[PDB]
Image: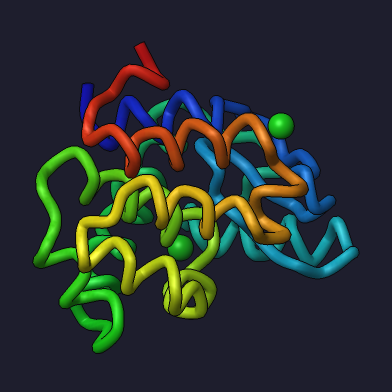
Length: 162
Ligand SMILES: [Cl-]
Ligand SMILES: [Cl-]
């Protein structure tokens, strides 16, 4: 299993502009287009992202290209963040994917705000970090996904996804 397959599972694949769980305009494999409530606005960001007049529909290749770019931006992001880097550096391979998953979803800023859980991850106190992670809006609004991520951090294995 690997991060791409992992997120492909958490995000799914949609070729037409849709509303995510928070109600924002997204496409592809979890690619957020805009937080704005305007469809045209969303349409414009898409055209711009893709580089063509899309009319809100893309192809698989196109979805995949944005997904490559977004996973890349996420890794880089983490590696560029003073708070996230040290954590990432401390982890093993599986768990590193789990951290990428969260930053993909919420952004660096978002994740960098889990101060406490982060410190617990750095310290390798898996069951404690897991409990702390669950005490969050993130967990409360997306229980199933958060559980998978959390179990990965707890176990260091891919069982939640197998
Ligand atoms: Cl983009
Ligand atoms: Cl859920």
